[PDB]
Image (cartoon, rainbow, N blue to C red):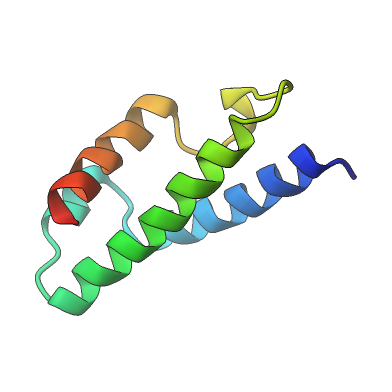
Length: 83
């Protein structure tokens, strides 16, 4: 399959796994241990890089991705405060 489709499949697997750890934005806010905060930062950095990478294709369509843009931005605000 084409490069874009490959990366979308990877992003979506990463996301469903991310979501099984941090189901909502507020759940990130509730993290207490530093290991958990680090886990979230590291996971979210990798999703964030892969998301930017798929936006670097002509065929990019947000609908192709798990997690809406706005919701993703809301996790990103937490990540920016947290890192």
